Image (cartoon, grey):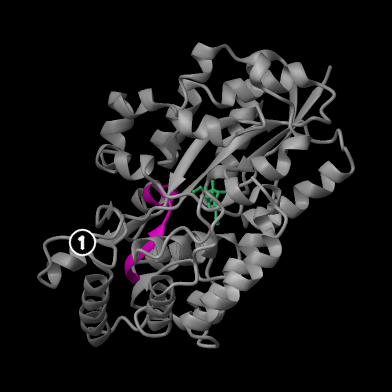
């Protein structure tokens, strides 16, 4: 009978690829359906380029794709509309915000699978060791704490020790980190939901200059090449006071044999001042049935299974990845394993989106401009003031004649 083939999460990032292949295998066994799993590059933007090859070919060789929250506007032509396959009641079990994200010109491109938001990881043993009782609320405090702890730990002989790791590589992850920087300085959303390209302002410039100020000082020089896992590795080996990253890093840091098991917490990222907004970039992945699948009924069944309560529960318990079902945030087992889901839920719900809705199908071009201009500040090649002006100009060109 049919072979349902799934291009899912990458085995190069955390345990998501292995766990998803397992879930797909379980559905295959449960229903007596053959399945195959197709692996992917680590970085989202490289995965998009891979999958676009299949879509351009109208290839039947993948039935189900795991797609980024930033993609629906890009991928819609290649998605089977799921709206007819779900009742209103079923669809309301997901966060409406993510359903809406995934709905393009009325077409439900994909089911919400797990959400995501940027957060601050901090070593609580080290904060306590150096007389700090709370994680930093301001970027200035993060700097001051990082400098003092780094000076201490280096003096004690850990030459591998740094104050802060983050995603500074030129790729989509840096757009994520930069939106957080910019938004948390009161510099806006880069491109606002109404289409206004707002990034050329003094607050956004300062946010970028501040980030430059970290590189080779409180963060490694090599941070300009770090994606999620490079940052996680330094952090997880015990060599960073702080890390910006997504929720998945929590379960991995708690695993038996982690050098940092039991020594960290998470909180909202810091911000420039008390009146700035909290910044957490909205991420997360969705489940799309291919418009080119020869087996839409079966593929929809698998996608509904993957997006079910019990699979999302397993995702949350074992991989600390965020449900797209509000009911799971009151599940006793989810909360007992991840108590930080409770206090950060409103951070997750208030996560700031990248400009994928307003840029639509041109989002990837916009983001490439953002990360390349941000990266030029991190490297010390441009100041934030020039970079934001240049970025405005590039985004104006990219979005000229695009209306949302
Ligand atoms: O790099 C930006 C990208 O980050 C996140 O997806 C990448 C991987 O992160 C996970 O560990 C989940 O946090 C894996 O499951 C992902 O493959 C984020 O969710 C995206 O929205 C974002 O574009």
202 left or right, relative to 225: left
Percent x, y for residue 234? 42, 69
Percent x, y for residue 339? 26, 38
Identified at 22% across, 77% down, the residue is 144
Foreground residue, 24 or 287?
Answer: 287
Q: Is residue 128 above or below residue 117?
A: below
Residue hosting label 1: 274
Does the magenta segment cover residue 249? yes
Q: Is residue 244 above or below residue 40?
A: below
232 left or right, relative to 404: left
Work out whether residue 38 can be spotted: no
Mark 1 nearby-residue class (10 Å; few <14, some 14–19, many ≥20): few
Chain part drawn in magenta: 239-250
Foreground residue, 289 or 363?
Answer: 363
Q: Quadrant of residue 366?
A: bottom right
Q: Is residue 27 above or below residue 133?
A: above
């Amino acid at each position: 009978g049919p072979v349902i083939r799934v291009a899912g999460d990458s085995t190069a990032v955390g345990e998501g690829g292995r766990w998803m292949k397992e879930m797909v295998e379980a559905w295959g066994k449960k229903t007596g359906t053959r399945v195959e799993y197709i692996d992917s590059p680590a970085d989202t933007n490289d995965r998009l380029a891979l999958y676009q090859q299949y879509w351009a070919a109208r290839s039947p060789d993948v039935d189900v794709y795991m797609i980024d929250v930033i993609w629906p506007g890009i991928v819609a032509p290649h998605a089977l509309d799921l709206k007819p396959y779900l009742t209103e009641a079923e669809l309301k079990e997901f966060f409406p915000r993510i359903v809406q994200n995934n709905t393009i010109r009325g077409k439900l491109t994909s089911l919400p699978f797990f959400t995501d938001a940027g957060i601050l990881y901090y070593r609580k043993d080290l904060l306590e060791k150096y007389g700090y009782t709370s994680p930093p609320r301001t970027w200035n405090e993060l700097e001051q704490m990082a400098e003092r702890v780094m000076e201490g730990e280096r003096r004690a002989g850990n030459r591998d020790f740094w104050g802060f790791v983050f995603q500074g590589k030129p790729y989509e992850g840096l757009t994520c980190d930069a939106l957080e920087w910019i938004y948390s300085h009161g510099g806006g959303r880069i491109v606002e939901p109404d289409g206004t390209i707002s990034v050329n302002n003094g607050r956004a410039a300062l946010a970028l200059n501040r980030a430059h100020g970290w590189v080779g000082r409180i963060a490694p020089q090599g941070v300009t090449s770090y994606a999620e896992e490079e940052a996680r590795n330094v952090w997880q080996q015990g060599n960073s006071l702080f890390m910006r990253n997504w929720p998945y890093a929590y379960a991995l840091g708690q695993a038996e044999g982690s050098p940092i098991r039991g020594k960290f917490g998470v909180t909202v990222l810091p911000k420039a001042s008390a009146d700035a907004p909290n910044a957490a970039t909205l991420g997360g992945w969705q489940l799309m049935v291919s418009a080119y699948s020869r087996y839409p009924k079966e593929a929809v069944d698998l996608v509904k299974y993957l997006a079910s309560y019990e699979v999302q529960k397993d995702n949350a318990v074992r991989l600390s990845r965020l449900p797209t079902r509000p009911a799971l945030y009151t599940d006793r087992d989810v909360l007992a394993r991840n108590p930080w889901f409770r206090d950060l839920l409103p951070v997750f719900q208030n996560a700031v989106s990248r400009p994928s809705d307003v840029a639509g199908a041109r989002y990837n071009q916009v983001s490439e401009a953002i990360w390349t201009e941000v990266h030029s500040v991190l490297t010390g090649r441009k100041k934030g003031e020039q970079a934001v002006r240049d970025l405005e100009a590039r985004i104006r060109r990219i979005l000229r004649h695009h209306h949302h």
